[PDB]
C-alpha cells in the first residue's frame, strides 16, 4: 500500500516542492498566478504551469493495482472583457518529465490539435475560448491524449469569482469525475467519464496545473490558483 | 480545534457505533438495508434510519465557530417497476435525540408536510416519488425544516445501479453542495445552496440516513447504503 | 475496512460527544478536569472518567480482523505536596457500557485488586501512589484485567508540567506501546508488552480516561487532560 | 497552512518518488536495501541513501512559522557476527541538494568528524560500531551538524529482528523525540532533545535514510527499511 497527500491553503513565495514552468509566479497574496499580469492587467500570449515536485504512483505493474485519487482546488479567472476571454486552465496528469507545449488554445498541454496515445496526458480543462475543435460556448472538458475533449459540458464563467473544483478517480469503475461550484452564485457543474488510467498513463506521473492567455492582445484573462489539496492511495492486491 | 472522522467500506452485523432505527438491518453482503426485503422483494410501508452513534459538533457558541464537513457514500435503489418507484432516501442532520417520523413521502424525517423551525432538520433527499408538494419527476433536493425542498434538480434514477454521493458544507460561504455520480452510465448531477447551519441546527447533531418504501403495495423499492465516509472540522476562532 | 478518528486540541464546556462519568468537568480553560478542584485545591476521594461517545470497533469475528490504533494526549498532575501524591490517571479500553468502579488506588477501573477475565479492561496507568500490589516508586504500567500491572517502568512525576503521551497498538505483533515525554525537561519514558486484544476485549469498546485522588485528606492532586487525538483502523481481511 | 504526507507499507521495484543514492536497491520482497548484499551476504564498504523526492517545507521565513512532523518506519539489521557489526543506519533531514558523504562510521552524512553549522543536518542514528568519537557500546543518538551526537542512549541490537521507530518534532517546544521498539522481545528505547529546526535547517529539506557497512571485510551487516510513513504540518501564523 502507498499513499501520497499534500495540502496548500495558500502558496509561499519560493515553493521548492512545486515545479514552476513558463510564466508562473507566486503573488504577494499567496496565489499561484499561472499567466502573467503586468500593472494589474493580464498579459496576452502567456503560458504557465505548476506541478507537484514528487511523482505520484498511480498504478503498479508488479502488483497489478491502480490508485484512487481525489484533488480539490480553488481558482479565479478574471477577464477584463468577458466576451474576449481566452484561453483557460487545466488540471492534468502527465509523464514525470513533462514540459510545456504550445500556448493559446492548446493550453500548454499539446504540441498540436491531434490525438496521440504517446502524449500520456489526462486533463480536466476549463476552456474559455472556442477553438475550431471546441463545442459552442465556454465548457469544462475531460481530455485524454488530445485537446479535443472526450466529453464536455457547458460551463458559465462567473467572472472574478472563486471556483471550487473537485476531481476524483475511482479505479474500480475507471471513472474520472470533475465538479465545479461557485458558492457566490450557488451554481454548479459536474461531469464524469470512463478513463482507464492504467492503459493511458505511465506508472508514475506528475500532477498539476496549466493555463494560457489568448494569442491576440485583446483576448486576455488571469488564471490564478488559490489553494490545492491532493490525496492518492495505491492499494495492496486482493 | 476539533475534528471527527469515520470510514465504513462495508458494514458489520450489530454495528454498535451506529444507531439503527425502524426497519434497518445489515445484509450478509455488509450493506445497510434501510427498508425491508422479504423473499428477495422490497416490502411496502417500510421505514428505516441509521445514524452515527457519536454526536457531531457542527458549531460552537462559546467560540462563535462553525464546522466544515464532507461526507461520501454509495447507495443503490432497486425498484421492480421503475415507474412505480417510491419513496426515496436522504442523508440528514438532526438533533441528537432524533427519532423516526412519518413513513412514505415524508421519508421518516417529518411528522407532516409543513415547515417548522423547531424540526431542526437539514437533509439531502433522493426523491423517487412525486408527492403533492414535489416538483415534476424524480429529483435531488436540499431540505431545511420541511419536506418541501428549498432547492431541487432533476435526477433520473438508474435502477439497481450504484450511486456515489458527496455532500459538503463550507462554513465560510454557508454553502451545502450535493453531487451524485453513476459510474455505470457516466451520468452525474450536482446542486448547491446557502444553508446557515448555525441558524438552523443545534450545536451538536446526529448525522445519517433515512429511507422509506411506498405506502401502496405496488410502489416499492429497496434503499441500500454500501459504504460511508464522514469528516468534519471545527476550527479555532480567528 | 472501518476507521474512527477524532482530535480535540482543547475541550468545549458541554462536550456531548464525550461521556463524562463521576466528578469530571470541563474547565473554563478548556481542560478535562477529571478529579474535583474546590477553591483552587484538589479534593480527596474524587473519581472522574471521560469516554469518547462512539464505540470503537477493535476486532471483527465476521472477517477475523483486528484493529490497529494510536492515541496521543497531554495531561498535567499538580500535587500540592509531591510526597503525598495520589492516586493517578489512566487511559483505558473497556466494554461499551463501562461504569466507574472503586476509587483511590483502583483508579475507577476495578472493583477489587484481583485478576478477572470478565473485567475486559486494558489500561495504561500513570500511578502516583504505592499500593500493596505496586512496585517501588511512581510508575507507568500496562494493565490487563487487573490493577496489578503486567509490566511497569519507573516514572518521576514532574509536578504541574505538561506530559505528552502516545499509546499505540500493532495488531500484527499484538504489541501495546506507551511513551511519555516532558518537553520542559527533555525527559522521556517508554514501555511495551504483548496484549492480545481479540482475546481480552469485546468486539466494540469505549475508550478514554480515568483518574482518582487519594482516599485520605492530605493525599491529593489534580488530573487534567489538555488535548486528545485518537485513530483506529480495522482492516479488510487478507 | 501546508501539509505533506506519505505512506509506504512496502516498496515497489523502481520507486520514482524516492531519490536513491549510492548502493540502495529495492529487493524482490519490497524492502529498501540500503547496503549491498552479494550471494546472501552483506558487502563491506557499502553506503546507500534514500530520500523522499519532494522537498518538505519545515519552516517559513515569510510567516515566521515552523512545522511539526512525525515519521514512523520499520528496519532490520542482520550482522553475520554481532561482535563485528558496522556501521549503522540513520534517519535524517538535510538540504534539498544533499549528496552522500563519507562511508563507514560517518554514515554517508558527514565529510569528517567535526562540527560545522553549514552541514545543515539533523539525524537520528542507530550506531552499531564504536568510533573514536562514540560512547561505549551500540547506541541511538541525536546528531545536529556533526557525527558526534548531542545525546545518546544505550541500545542493544536484536540481530535480524524488526525494529519499529517513531521520530517526531514538536515545534512549540522545539523537541525532537525518537523511539525504537522490538515487538518480538518487548524491548524499547526513547530519547529526546531540544533542537531548533529554524536555526539549524534551511526552509526546505529532503528527508530519508542512510546506512553504511564497515570499512573492513569482516565488519558487515545489512540495513533494510521495510516500511515508512511521514506527516508534516506547517501551520498558519497567529
Ligand atoms: C506522438 O507523441 C510521441 C511521443 O512524444 C512523439 O514521438 C516522440 O517525438 C519526439 C519529438 O517531439 C522525439 O524526441 C526527439 O528526438 C530527437 C532526436 O533524437 C531530439 O533531437 C529531440 O530533442 C527530441 O527529444 C521522441 O523520440 C519521439 N518518441 C518516440 C517514442 O518515438 C510523436 O512524434 C512524431 O513521431 C516521432 C517518431 C518523430 O518523427 C517526431 O518528430 C514526430 O513528431 C508524436 N506523433 C505525432 C504525430 O505528433
Ligand atoms: C488574427 C490574429 O490577429 N491573430 C491570430 C493569429 O493569426 C495570425 C496572424 C499572423 C500570422 N503570421 O503568419 O504573422 C499568423 C497567424 O493566429 C493564431 C492561430 O489561429 C490566433 O490564435 C488564437 O487566438 C485566440 C485569441 O484571439 C485564442 O487565443 C485561440 O486559442 C488562438 N488559437 C490557437 C490555435 O491557439 C491569433 O488570434
Ligand atoms: C390508496 C391506497 O391504496 N393507498 C394510499 C393510502 O390509502 C390509505 C387508505 C386507508 C387508510 N386508512 O387509515 O384506513 C390509510 C391510507 O394513503 C396513503 C397516504 O396518503 C397513500 O400514500 C402515498 O402512497 C404513494 C405510493 O402509492 C407514495 O408512497 C406516497 O409518498 C404516499 N403518500 C404519502 C403522503 O406518504 C397510499 O397510496
Ligand atoms: C489511613 C487513612 O486515614 N485512611 C485509609 C482508610 O482506612 C480507614 C478505614 C476505616 C477508617 N475509619 O474512619 O474506621 C479510617 C481509615 O482505608 C483506605 C484503604 O481502603 C486507605 O486508602 C488509601 O489511601 C491512600 C492515600 O492515603 C491512597 O489513595 C491509596 O490508594 C488508598 N488505598 C486504596 C486501596 O484505594 C485510606 O487512606
Ligand atoms: C583495511 C583497513 O584497515 N581499513 C581501515 C582504514 O585503513 C586505511 C588505510 C589507509 C588509508 N589511507 O588514507 O591510505 C585510509 C584508511 O582506516 C579506516 C579509517 O580509520 C577504517 O575504517 C573503520 O573501519 C571500521 C570497521 O573495521 C568501521 O567501519 C569504522 O566506522 C571505520 N572508521 C571510519 C572513521 O569510518 C578501516 O577499517
Ligand atoms: C469475575 O467478575 C464478576 C463481577 O463482574 C464476579 O461476579 C465473578 O465471580 C464469579 O462469577 C460469579 C457470577 C459467581 O458465580 C461467583 O461465584 C464467581 O466467583 C468474578 N470471577 C471470579 C473468578 O472471581
Ligand atoms: C412546531 O411548531 C409548533 C408551534 O407552532 C409546536 O407546537 C411544535 O412543538 C413544533 N414542532 C416540533 C417541536 O417538532
Ligand atoms: C563547512 O561545510 C561546508 C559544506 O558542508 C564546506 O564547504 C566547508 O568547507 C566546511 N567548513 C569547514 C570544514 O570548516
Ligand atoms: Ca479552447
Ligand atoms: Ca416525494
Ligand atoms: Ca497505585
Ligand atoms: Ca559509530
Ligand atoms: Mn475545449
Ligand atoms: Mn421531494
Ligand atoms: Mn500501579
Ligand atoms: Mn555514534
Image (cartoon, coloured by chain):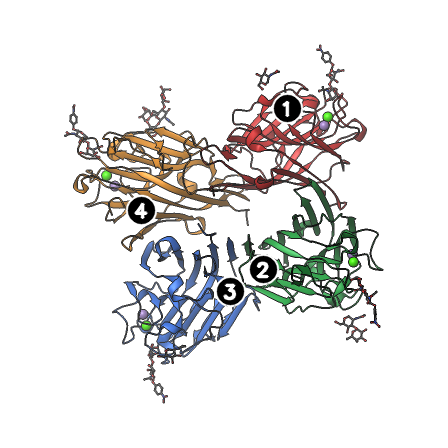
Chain colours: A orange, B blue, C green, D red
The residue where tag 2 is placed is: C27
Q: Which mark is residue D108?
A: 1
* Quadrant of the displayed image that contains ligand 13: top left
Q: Chain of mark 1?
A: D
> Residue drawn at (42%, 43%), measured in percent from left and top?
A9
Element carrying mark 4:
loop
Rendering quarter of residue C42: bottom right
> Is residue C67 visible in the rendered structure shown here?
no
Q: Residues within 10 Å of mark 2 (few under 14, many from 20)?
A: few
Q: Is residue A150 left or right of residue A58?
A: left
Q: Are marks 3 and 2 on the same chain?
A: no
In-front residue for pair A162/A97 = A162
Q: Using the numbered discs, state the Cα–Cα distance from disc 1 to disc 2 in whole angstroms.
A: 51 Å
Q: Using the numbered discs, state the Cα–Cα distance from disc 4 to disc 1 in whole angstroms.
A: 48 Å
Q: Are marks 4 and 2 on the same chain?
A: no
Q: Which mark is residue B55?
A: 3
Nearer mark to the viewer, of 1 and 2: 2
Amino acid at each position: 500500500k502507498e499513499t501520497t497527500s499534500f495540502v496548500f491553503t495558500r502558496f509561499s513565495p519560493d515553493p521548492q516542492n512545486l515545479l514552476l514552468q513558463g510564466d508562473t509566479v507566486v503573488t504577494s497574496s499567496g496565489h499561484l498566478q499561472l499567466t502573467q499580469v503586468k500593472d494589474g492587467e493580464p498579459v496576452y500570449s502567456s503560458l504557465g504551469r505548476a506541478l507537484y515536485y514528487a511523482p505520484i504512483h498511480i498504478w503498479d505493474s508488479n502488483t497489478d493495482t491502480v490508485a484512487n485519487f481525489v484533488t480539490s482546488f480553488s481558482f479565479v479567472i478574471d477577464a477584463p472583457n468577458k466576451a474576449k476571454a481566452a484561453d483557460g486552465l487545466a488540471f492534468f496528469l502527465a509523464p514525470v518529465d513533462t514540459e510545456p507545449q504550445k500556448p493559446g488554445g492548446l493550453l500548454g498541454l499539446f504540441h498540436d490539435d491531434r490525438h496521440n496515445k504517446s502524449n500520456h496526458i489526462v486533463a480536466v480543462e476549463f476552456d474559455t475560448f472556442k477553438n475550431s475543435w471546441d463545442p459552442e460556448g465556454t465548457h469544462i472538458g475531460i481530455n485524454v491524449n488530445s485537446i479535443v475533449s472526450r466529453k464536455t459540458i457547458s460551463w458559465d464563467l462567473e467572472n472574478d469569482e472563486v471556483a471550487n473544483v473537485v476531481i476524483s478517480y475511482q479505479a474500480s469503475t475507471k471513472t474520472l469525475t470533475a465538479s465545479l461550484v461557485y458558492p457566490s452564485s450557488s451554481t454548479s457543474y459536474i461531469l464524469n467519464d470512463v478513463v482507464d488510467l492504467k492503459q493511458i498513463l505511465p506508472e508514475y506521473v506528475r500532477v498539476g496545473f496549466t493555463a494560457a492567455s489568448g494569442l491576440s492582445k485583446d483576448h486576455v484573462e488571469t488564471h490564478d490558483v488559490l489553494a490545492w489539496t491532493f490525496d492518492s492511495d495505491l492499494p495492496d492486491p486482493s
